Length: 195
Ligand code: NA
Ligand code: NA
Image 1: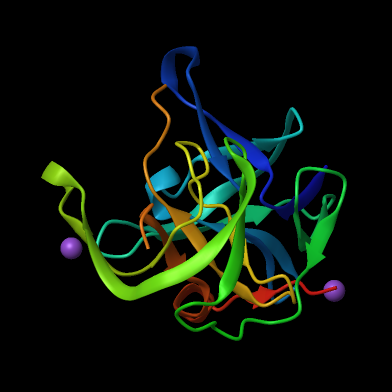
Image 2: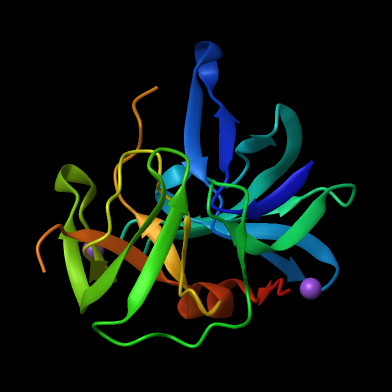
């Protein structure tokens, strides 16, 4: 199977239920293949399917306080250093220069597909009720829906920005949040796949 930023992955849960989330960025750890995503999506040990096929398992997850995780992908699968735009194209990943407030950014995920907007605030804390809070999030006004969680945020020029932080699917003025990608890469020791 092919792992690309923004696409759906599925998580087999107990009693035949299935969780849905979106790929953030394909990464390598040494020669290990993987992808970064949201920690709200799963805990370590959660199996992961893409395109109907077992592709890997969550390796680490840190939520709340942060909202980050990464999945180890089996060696037989192909990593694409790009983010799908859901309409036949992709944005090639070039690096992770963090963009400023006001910068144009697009996010990709399986519920609302590819939606674009601008960054409006940084270092925001979001309240998750009984779970506690997540701090340090960047806010933007892009459209988003439940299930986009974990998916890619990238500038058109290809600089990776972050991972959608938001609600799970049950199994400026819009306010949408993402987890910054550079702290995630650093914590887990991950290198972005580029193209
Ligand atoms: Na917190
Ligand atoms: Na590459």
